[PDB]
Image (tube, helix red, strand yellow):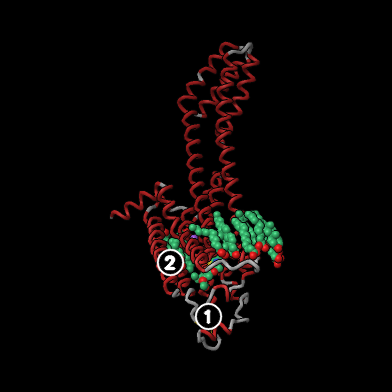
Amino acid sequence: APPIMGSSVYITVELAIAVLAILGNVLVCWAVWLNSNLQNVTNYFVVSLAAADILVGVLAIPFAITISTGFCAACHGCLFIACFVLVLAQSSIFSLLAIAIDRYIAIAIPLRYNGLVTGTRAAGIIAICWVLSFAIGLTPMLGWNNCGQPKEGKAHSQGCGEGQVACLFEDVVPMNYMVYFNFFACVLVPLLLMLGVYLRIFAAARRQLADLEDNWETLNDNLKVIEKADNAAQVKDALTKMRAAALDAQKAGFDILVGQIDDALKLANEGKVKEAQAAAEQLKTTRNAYIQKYLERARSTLQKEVHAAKSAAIIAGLFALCWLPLHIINCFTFFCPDCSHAPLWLMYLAIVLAHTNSVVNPFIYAYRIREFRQTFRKIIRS
Ligand SMILES: CC(C)CCC[C@@H](C)[C@H]1CC[C@H]2[C@@H]3CC=C4C[C@@H](O)CC[C@]4(C)[C@H]3CC[C@]12C
Ligand SMILES: CC(C)CCC[C@@H](C)[C@H]1CC[C@H]2[C@@H]3CC=C4C[C@@H](O)CC[C@]4(C)[C@H]3CC[C@]12C
Ligand SMILES: CC(C)CCC[C@@H](C)[C@H]1CC[C@H]2[C@@H]3CC=C4C[C@@H](O)CC[C@]4(C)[C@H]3CC[C@]12C
Ligand SMILES: CCCc1cc2c(=O)c(-c3nc(C)cs3)c(C)oc2cc1OC(C)=O
Ligand code: NA
């Protein structure tokens, strides 16, 4: 069956993917430019990630279409077109890892976040990461390639010239580089690291949203204890505890609260039980009017952070889902030489799926993040 029909389907699909990758990601980048509420450090990594996807459509996809033809080319030029996508995938990994870390900093140490994670430090990190991405992805160009052992029988059959090879990914890029260096070290390890960062993010969230609840219960149970108490010393016990739990909430209305606990304690230390109890009853007014509003705000903010962290995790998860099959196929090719090579149709499918990852991010932002969604609408409307 003529190779141009099988190759026609693959190519059309690649072109559809490129179109969509470019479109969606230009809109991400355009949204961040226009909306100042989307101008934060997290979103600069998002933009870097969008840039990489734009380049998959503009460059990586045309390169892959090109190399699918097996056209004659100087080996090192062939190399470049085979490996450029690795640079883009690496850049993406760095961006995803940074987003995970950024979100972890925001939830673990919100006090120090703004001064630690600035836009200036973020742009420097992005630049460094792009340089590193070029180094990792283009490592084969530094000598780890099969250009030294060309398939001359395959090159002579297609009438290639001197110094040229039939340009095919697996003929030029060593599988050991693909499996051990690229997959294990540069993809798998950073993905496992991301998994770990997200676990810590979700656990820290759980611990804080438990802690908020505990402190509130403490305030309410110590009120009851004070309400039915025998003497002044019991009242003093329950307000000494209450005081400490109000000062931790203030670090993590409060002027009034501590003050009122203090009023009650002085009375309690003078042996006046009924007066201490009545003064402690006034604490209820403060709890309703201020403290409960703080508990519910703080809770809301933590829920917003968990949601935003889930959205970022989904993105990282989708990268793994889209890229893993191609990596897994490479493992079979490398580790199992007695196994028949995965068919060309499957290679095409795995490649296309990897490329499809460059289309997905804009949809996740639209479905999961209000500010992006609202800005996408205005850009589209106008
Ligand atoms: C959830 C996602 C990440 C998992 C996807 C796993 C895919 C990539 C796995 C599942 C079954 C696997 C196939 C099982 C059997 C063979 C026959 C062998 O001669 C070549 C590899 C090949 C064809 C494997 C290629 C990879 C494969 C298709
Ligand atoms: C979920 C994460 C850890 C994904 C990474 C899992 C990868 C590395 C695993 C999953 C399935 C595994 C393959 C299963 C079967 C074979 C056939 C055997 O003859 C050689 C090893 C080989 C080819 C394995 C290599 C490693 C492999 C591809
Ligand atoms: C994190 C998880 C998913 C990794 C799982 C990797 C598993 C599937 C890998 C790790 C070590 C691998 C084995 C290592 C050695 C051999 C000998 C070879 O003659 C046949 C395949 C076989 C028997 C492999 C089968 C797949 C294997 C068991
Ligand atoms: C059809 C597009 C060209 C092409 C690209 C690739 C390719 O991009 C990879 C990659 N694997 C990873 C992990 C990242 S990229 C592999 C293993 O085989 C390929 C084989 C290819 O087709 C030929 C016949 O040359
Ligand atoms: Na990407």
Query: Which of the numbered marks, if any, corresponds to residue 124?
Result: none
Label 1 CA crowd tier, 10 Å (few <14, some 14–19, many 20+): many
Query: Which of the numbered marks, if any, corresponds to residue 166?
Result: 1
Residue name at image x 44 percent, y 70 percent: 6
Q: Quadrant of residue 248?
A: top right
Residue type of the residue flagged with mark 1:
Ala
Q: Is mark 1 within 8 Å of ligand 4?
A: no
Decide: is 166 above or below 207.
below
- In the shown orientation, is residue 378 left or right of residue 263? left
Residue type of the residue flagged with mark 2:
Glu
Residue 154: where, in percent of width, then height?
55, 82
Q: Which residue is mark 2?
A: 14
- In the shown orientation, is residue 7 left or right of residue 182? left
Query: The C terminus is located in which quarter?
Result: bottom left
Residue at the farthest left position: 382
* Real-space CA distance between mark 1 and mark 2, rounded to the nearest whole angstrom: 21 Å
Residue 278: where, in percent of width, then height?
53, 14
Mark toward the start of the polypeptide (1 vs 2): 2
Work out whether residue 122 can be spotted.
no
- In the shown orientation, is residue 214 left or right of residue 63? right
- In the shown orientation, is residue 100 left or right of residue 184? left
Decide: is 48 above or below 205.
below
Residue 121: where, in percent of width, then height?
53, 58
Residue name at image x 50 percent, y 21 percent: 284
Q: In this rendered view, identify the residue nearer to me: 48 or 150.
A: 150
Work out whether residue 274 can be spotted.
yes
Query: The N terminus is located in which quarter?
Result: bottom left
Q: Quadrant of residue 191?
A: bottom right
